[PDB]
Length: 129
Ligand SMILES: Cc1cn([C@H]2C[C@H](OP(=O)(O)O)[C@@H](COP(=O)(O)O)O2)c(=O)[nH]c1=O
Ligand SMILES: [Ca+2]
Image 1 (cartoon, rainbow, N blue to C red):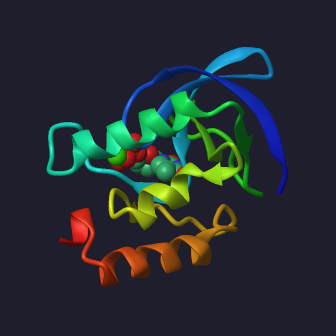
Image 2 (image 1 turned 120 degrees about the horizontal axis):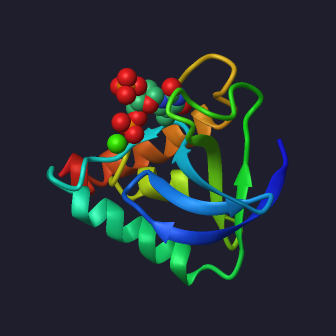
C-alpha cells in the first residue's frame, strides 16, 4: 500500500470527510471502522476528534487498500493519515470507533486496528466505558 496526497476540503463526521484527491472533490469513508452517528452517544466526540486531527494536520494523505476504492455511494474507501498518524487507528485507539466493515481483500490494517480496539476496551475508554 502507498500513501498519496490529498487536501482537506471539509469535515463531515466521525468517519467521512471531503478531500481533494487528484484534484477532484470526493467524500472519503474510513476503511475498517464505524463511528456513532452524530445523533448517538459519542457521535459528537468522534466527529470532533476526527475534525481536529484533520484540520490541525499539515499534510493529509490517503492510502487505498488492495480492493474496491469507491463504495456503492461513490465514497472513496481509504486509510487516512494526518501528519503520518492514521485517523482510522486513532479513532479506534480512543474508543471513538469500533472495528467494523471488514471485507476480504480490503483489510490490510485489520489486525493493527483490532489491537487498538483491545487497548481502548482494556482502558474502558469512551464507547467501552
Ligand atoms: C466502510 C464501508 C462501508 N460500505 C457500505 C456498507 C454499508 O452499506 P449500507 O448503507 O447499505 O448499510 C455502508 C456503511 O456506511 P456508513 O457507516 O457510513 O453508513 O457503507 C462499503 O460498502 N464498504 C466499506 O468498506
Ligand atoms: Ca458511521
